[PDB]
Image 1 (cartoon, rainbow, N blue to C red):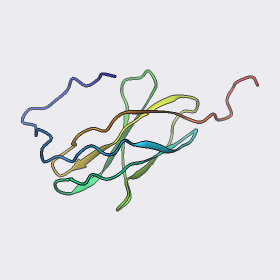
Image 2: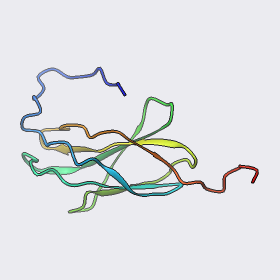
Image 3: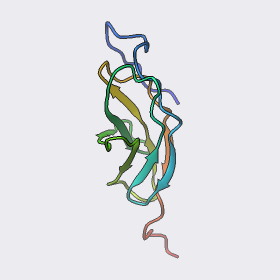
Image 4: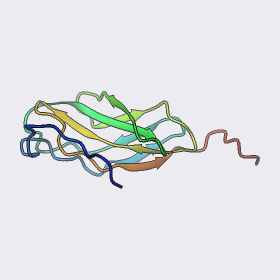
Length: 119
């Protein structure tokens, strides 16, 4: 796994930035959506607005971005996915400063939904 080669000038050395979240694990995965649960960062260094969760289909390079969590919850359910397909979910903390350390990219295979398989 190697992808990124990106960066901006005058950027903070992940000092006053929030530490990467706990290895996000697929507590609950569905055929259409996939829920994820992770622990909040102890050192936010300011005030966190929300958590950004990415998701992309196998092969493809780009990915969407869904940021929306409850007031006091680090759980976010991502829907509108494709069944019988490997997806790569991620998690990032966006605080006053900005996006701190990026979490580890996980791979979850959606559950089989009315698969075309001939028996």
